[PDB]
Image (cartoon, rainbow, N blue to C red; front, side, top):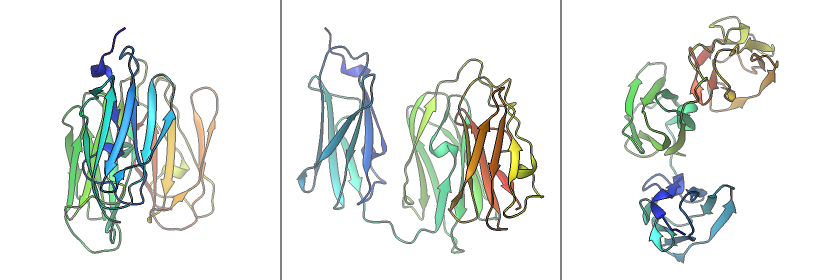
Length: 288
């Protein structure tokens, strides 16, 4: 027909051994296209026995799943294609209690996705002023090379590099415990041919080191004519973890007229990724 479970992949935060906490949605996807004629079965076993599992057909042999852990402890996720375990099934998942006082937060394109052979980066900035020890590790189809530089500013930049497509688990640890939402599931894509995230320049008043005022429409342009075709993502937030609104007008030629309005003369951070990869100079730290 013929059944071939080795062509199946099971990825998602709901399958990671550590990091998931109670009252969180534990999500994961299963890829089955190309695995021949078969049958997918997903079971989640917790300390309370059977766990409810919501399934959603994502098209093209991809199926999304969500279970909702309520009590800490060990959960087992069994994923089978024609009676044979898929990938690393069964998955042992240790669900923790509600996270305590967060001393640090993390955001950036490298926590959500990236491109093969390209740098996947994010930033980890301090909450308050109680200093500790930050830990980083990345698990996936290949061993990523991690680099992070303490900046004293309280926000230190983190980068990891790989050369294999797939989903990676990025762990940010504060005093040897996964911070909230850690591990972060990054979807690393294979590089399009014409796509050059390098050379995607973003100039403008809204991105300069100085010169941005509060309640002013701080604009900037993202010229990307020789960068292939790939989605543009603009994300802005202040010194706290609070996002502020961005507006991205596709001007139709390959350039973009981007706008965001700050609402505090406090330092904002504007991240511009092209095809899931930080363009040069991003993260833009703007003294608004």
